[PDB]
Image (tube, rainbow over all chains, first blue to last red; front, side, top):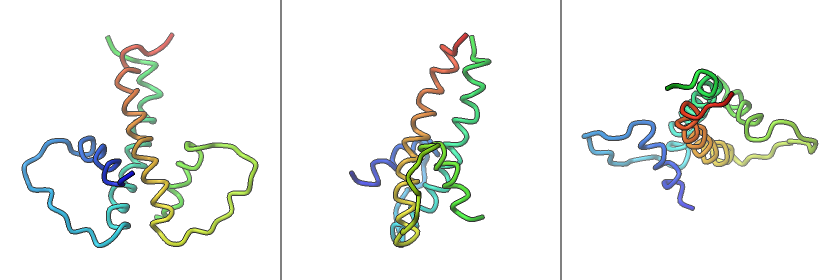
Amino acid sequence: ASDDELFSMLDQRFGGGEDLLMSGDNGMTEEKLRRYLKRTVTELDSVTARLREVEHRAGE
Amino acid sequence: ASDDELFSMLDQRFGGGEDLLMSGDNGMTEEKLRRYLKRTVTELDSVTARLREVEHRAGE
């Protein structure tokens, strides 16, 4: 499966909707793996971090 | 900060506890970034995905 497909899911979550052209000029694989991964672990850690409380407090 | 520090938390979340030696023999940065990124994306896309319902349904 194309890596872009997975990264696409992040494109919307990390910053869905915009105006400026996304364009593209990544040096290699790491370049993309740098921002998406560094961000993913944090986002991944974020959802899980709040998820523990979300189930507890919840919301009407 | 070392990348492993970030990939470590993922190590426990992606599969905490085991038996077989983790070892190590990654070609470069990508190699690690290949699994950790691709995973954390859906991983974050997962928690984020259920969190929306968790707040709602929650649990006694």
